[PDB]
Image: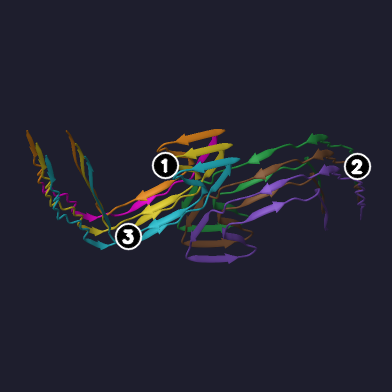
Chain colours: A orange, B yellow, C cyan, D green, E brown, F purple
């Protein structure tokens, strides 16, 4: 008996974002009101929690581009 | 018996973000009001918590670009 | 019996962010009001907590670019 | 000829405000956003103006009572 | 000819404000945002102006009481 | 001819403010943001102006009481 595996995922992918001018951006908010009333909080194993938040975000990238690329290979004899 | 594995994921991927000018960005907020009333907080094993927050963010990258790239290989005889 | 493994993930990936001028950025906030009322906090094993925060961020990188790249290889006979 | 005038407005008026306890008063506002854009302002002769205001008032008198009382007498021969 | 005038406005008016306890007063505001953009301001003759204001007031008199009382007499022969 | 005037406005007015305890007063504000942009300001003859102000007031009199009382008499022959 004999097993043989080859793995050659060749790739050449271009992500582009040609852009002129981003111009005038106004993020002008009049902050409201948040109330949270809890008693008990038991968190375990990869918990991500957000409890009571008033957050403002001006995310202005001059071109934002993500390439995600995973290669998995599991061998079980 | 004989097992043989080759692993050659070849890649050449370009991420680009040509940009002129980012211009005028105004992030002008009038901060609100946050109240949290808790009693007990038991956290364990990779907990990420945010309790009561009033946060303002001007994230202006002059071109932001992420390439994520994972290569995994698990061999089980 | 004989096992043989080769591992040659060759790569040449370019991340670029050509940019003119970042211009005028104004982050002008009128700070609000945060109240947190807790009693007990038991944290254990890789806890990240933020309790009661009023934070302001002007993150203006002149081009910010991240490349994440992990290579994993687990062999089990 | 002869003119004669008498003026005797007699009065005894009581204003009262018997009160126990004023208790818990909460004035908890999350301040908003006011913008005024003008060019020219010509004011004359007993002008009272308020231009662009974000004001908060906790007026808690422990009994507030006003008595206004005017006596006018104009004689024209 | 003969003119005769008498002026005897007699008065005995009591203003009262019996009160126990003023208690807990909370004036807790998260300050907002005011912008005024003008060019020209010509004021004359008893002008009262307020241009761009963010003001907070806790007026807690332990009993506030006003009595206004005017007596006018104009004689024209 | 003969003119005769008498002026005897007799008065005995009491203002009172009996009070126990003023208690707990909290004036806790998170200061906002005021911007005024003007060019020209020509004021004349009893002008009262307030331009751009962020003011906080805890006025807690232990009983505040005003009596205003004017007596006017104009004679024109």
Q: Is disc 3 placed on a helix, strand or loop?
A: loop
User: How dense is the environment of label 2, judged by Cα within 10 Å: few (below 14), some, or many (20 and up)?
Assistant: some
Q: Position of residue E39 (x, y in %)?
A: 46, 61
Left or right, E11 with reference to A13: right
Cα separation between marks 1 and 3:
30 Å
C77 or C72, which is in the foreground? Answer: C77
Q: Can you see residue A38? A: no
Q: Nearer the viewer, mark 1 or mark 3?
A: 1
Q: Is residue A20 magenta?
A: yes
Above/below status of C58 relative to A52? below
Cα separation between marks 1 and 2:
77 Å
Chain of the residue displaying label 2: E
Q: Is residue C77 magenta?
A: no
D9 or F5, which is in the foreground? Answer: D9
Q: Mark 1 near mark 2, Cβ–Cβ under 8 Å? A: no
Q: Mark 1 near mark 3, Cβ–Cβ under 8 Å? A: no
Left or right, B2 with reference to E8: left
Q: Which residue is mark 3?
A: C61
D19 or E49, which is in the foreground? Answer: D19
| Magenta-drawn segment | A11-37
Q: Nearer the viewer, mark 3 or mark 2?
A: 3
Above/below status of D11 relative to C62? above
Q: Can you see residue A16? A: yes
Residue B46 disc label: 1
Q: Is disc 2 placed on a helix, strand or loop?
A: loop
Cα separation between marks 3 and 2:
76 Å
Q: Nearer the viewer, mark 1 or mark 2?
A: 1
Q: Position of residue A42 (x, y in %)?
A: 50, 34
Q: Is disc 1 placed on a helix, strand or loop?
A: loop
Q: Position of residue D62 (x, y in %)?
A: 77, 41
Left or right, F46 with reference to A3: right
């Amino acid at each position: 008996g004999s097993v043989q595996i080859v793995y050659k995922p060749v790739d050449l992918s271009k992500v582009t974002s040609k852009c002129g001018s981003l111009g005038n951006i106004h993020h002008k908010p009049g902050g409201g009101q948040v109330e949270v009333k809890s008693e008990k909080l038991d968190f375990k194993d990869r918990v991500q929690s957000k409890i009571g938040s008033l957050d403002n975000i001006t995310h202005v990238p001059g071109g934002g581009n993500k390439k995600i690329e995973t290669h998995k290979l599991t061998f079980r004899e």
